Length: 69
Length: 69
Image (spheres, rainbow over the protein chains, first blue to last red):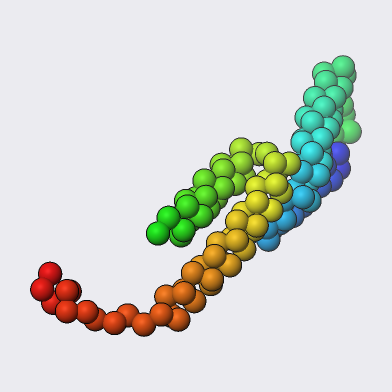
């Protein structure tokens, strides 16, 4: 429910920018992009873990409204 | 005459080190390698430009010793 797509897009754009800057002979700006990508990946992993942990707390039982729908 | 090779051999090591560092996810050390490569290329170009002037200035007279040899 719109939790991980936004983080995935931020990783994708940073990866594309780093790939574009590699061929441009821009080594000074690549370290910041690499650090930002690593931080984004760590945050994405933490968000995925905390999202999948919260689902096990409750049970997705079936009520009479779902069958009627 | 130990003037062109001594500088040409210094380019391959720097290029290989930069290529290895790029694939090693180490973008912090690449700036120094790029700067050193640029400085070495400038020095090599200046040496190559100044080396041919002496050869062009002199005349390659064909002596009779070469025919005998």
